[PDB]
Amino acid sequence: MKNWKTSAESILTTGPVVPVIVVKKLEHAVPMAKALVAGGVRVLEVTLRTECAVDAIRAIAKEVPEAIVGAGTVLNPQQLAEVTEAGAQFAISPGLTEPLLKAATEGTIPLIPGISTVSELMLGMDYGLKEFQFFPAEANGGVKALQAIAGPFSQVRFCPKGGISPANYRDYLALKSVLCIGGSWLVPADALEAGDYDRITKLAREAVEGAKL
Amino acid sequence: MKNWKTSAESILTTGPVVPVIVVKKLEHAVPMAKALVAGGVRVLEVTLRTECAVDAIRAIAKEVPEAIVGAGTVLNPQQLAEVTEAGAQFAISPGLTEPLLKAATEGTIPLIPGISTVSELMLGMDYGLKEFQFFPAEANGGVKALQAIAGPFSQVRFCPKGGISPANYRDYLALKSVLCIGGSWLVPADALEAGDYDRITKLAREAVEGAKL
Amino acid sequence: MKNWKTSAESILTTGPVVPVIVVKKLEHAVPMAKALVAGGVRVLEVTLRTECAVDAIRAIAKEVPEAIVGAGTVLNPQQLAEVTEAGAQFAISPGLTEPLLKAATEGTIPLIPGISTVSELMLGMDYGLKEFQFFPAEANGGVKALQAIAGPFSQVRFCPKGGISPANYRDYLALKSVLCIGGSWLVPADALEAGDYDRITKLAREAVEGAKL
Image 1: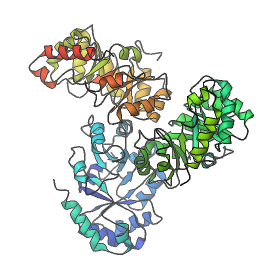
Image 2 (image 1 turned 180 degrees about the horizontal axis):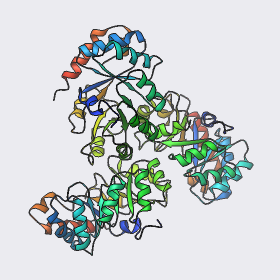
Image 3 (image 1 turned 45 degrees about the vertical axis):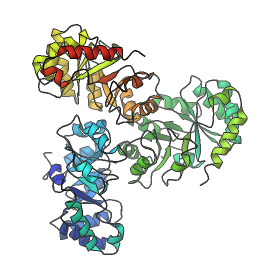
Image 4 (image 1 turned 90 degrees about the horizontal axis):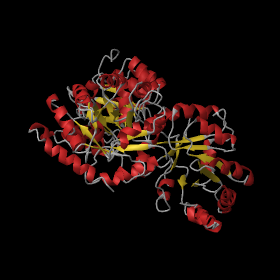
């Protein structure tokens, strides 16, 4: 997009795993982001599912500048403008809509919207997008489904998310159309609340390592 | 909606089961609605799949005022206006479209549209809807798929329909996002053909009973 | 459509099988189209997946009067206008979008767009379409899924495509809503190189024959 400083592609090629974080206790946002970076993971998706989500993005955005923090669960222009003002570097949505796609493309940060069908993908392509999230990965039919959908579009790249785990993520990563995946196991809600940051750094390290081949 | 007397939520919380009725002979509409009410089921979805569907709705509307009669298979604004004039108290559609979503929200009765993807759900939410039908439930990937889709939306409630039976409906009912399900087995075409209204009342009773827990 | 000379229905009732052709070398377009016609197959879908796809359509369109050549993989109005100018008699898309449906319906050739959900089908019906492609057939849940989706729409007809083979195509053809299927096995990428057009004609013959009942 003529309006995006950083491309959606760069966001997804930074690493094989994008942690989908849920922050309960704002106080744990920064130490958490640092634990992940120490583990090799710098692209963080902070989902708008808690009251402090936006503040978490703003905090991380300024105290851990080495991290590329973004917003998750962006459902409409209002939230897009909100996380953009808070310092998010990218936004991810479980699905797409014209209003959201129109705000995104006129906005200043890349949006990587999720799709389940070829039509939704084509709608997204109508606005010039090439990077999408495949959601809910598993529910949509996993790897075989994605291969069927991706088939006709060589230039399109995806970030599968939904029911993906250490047990299956290499299966998605092995696809040509897949740049990375969305994993929510790098930050257990328990370890977060418990301030157990070493657990988090270990998970990230292993995630990254287990991605090779 | 500022234009809806009764909410879509009330329609779905009335009972765990919503029978999806197909009427081929107008003469059986009233005696059928009464059989279901006698069995504990008062929310009836009369699908626009037969020539007498609308007349069936109008008849039930006055012959059985204890029943909340609605229309099913509403595909466009024309049919919405039609069943609304005939006395339908609610409308259900296998899918959604902006023309239909706009029409419904300006209209006077609640529309509970079906969705299969997050994008379709988000389009529906753009018009303020919170109650949707999950169709075709099974074909879309059943309970696991619905859980994936529902996940990001705590305030949204569904009414799964499509391939649901006595054998699996408690699985859907057990979900927090599910208020009720669409069942088409309460009115066996035959039973009706053989005017076994007692068969119908028995099925309804059992359906309701088998829903507890 | 008031603007379409030939209907989308005629395109699909011409034969039980519509070959989805991939042409890499323009020199094989005409001899190939003739091989298929000799085998009984006259409706050809030349997919826009190679540089010479459009030239192949133009060549066949003028060289082989006994066939009905169309374009496949049409993703937007630009390509629709392009294949229309090249002589395509119909266009097929893996999905649908309002820009494409609007351009198509204002255009002069029938578009048979693919769908996976009821909503996408309803969007297509909003523009007056009745013939659709079911894609990706298998990935969407095959015959059971299609039956679920087709159910509420008696007037709608489909052309399943995606994972369909000589092993399952009669299963789809057996459905009342199905007029024909998209098969990509009538033209082996190999048969083209060695220039074994007889192999192609044999496959077409067998395809047609194996469709009876």
